[PDB]
Length: 262
Ligand SMILES: [Cl-]
Ligand SMILES: [Cl-]
Ligand SMILES: [Cl-]
Ligand SMILES: [Cl-]
Image 1 (cartoon, rainbow, N blue to C red):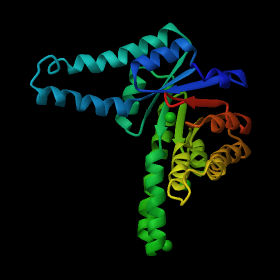
Image 2: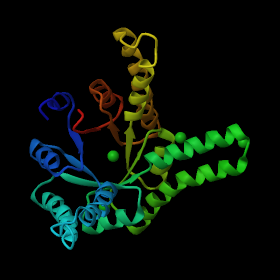
Image 3: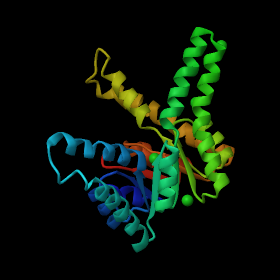
Image 4: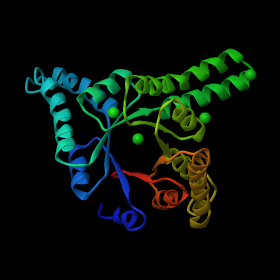
């Protein structure tokens, strides 16, 4: 936020902050974040392993009080929902976590299809390499596991359903299933692009990294441009690169997701 107001200077409107840390979430709330993105599944995994530490360390301050820690995490976020117009977006790939977040209170439910979409993509390509049509069908069911969560949330009456992926084809299909907010996550493309310049014979070449990271940016913006042609309205963009987020606003993304890395 000490360096995010540059995005607030141009266009602005909607800024989302992604974190599971309460201190950063509170500071983002006070700094004017329009949407807070909290991972209900990441908070659950840290919970089921917290009381596991209390069983290992030899301490009773943690055992029989872990249920108080979990409920406390829900309450501090729900209190933020009341005190302001800042929206709380809960994200998970797990159906029980989504219904729990809906019960606890959520303005946006984000069906996370990023990992499952990538696993389906690698299974499809692996099936093509093996010439196995059965593995093709296996790969397709890995994506429909996330689309079915979207359409079931639509059937039960969820108001604001979101979907996270890295590819416009998965997001368009989720959009047809009932998702209204399409989240493009471009962090992996920048990560892979930077990992490749480190493998070159001249990795310190400051000229050869500029366009390689740029090509990874155009691949992200291309997802936004194609979704804009299909007719999508609310498009969100996730990236840890400053130029990637700024230019994505001009491409058609009206929600920019920042985090502590920015
Ligand atoms: Cl095949
Ligand atoms: Cl909702
Ligand atoms: Cl997200
Ligand atoms: Cl895909």
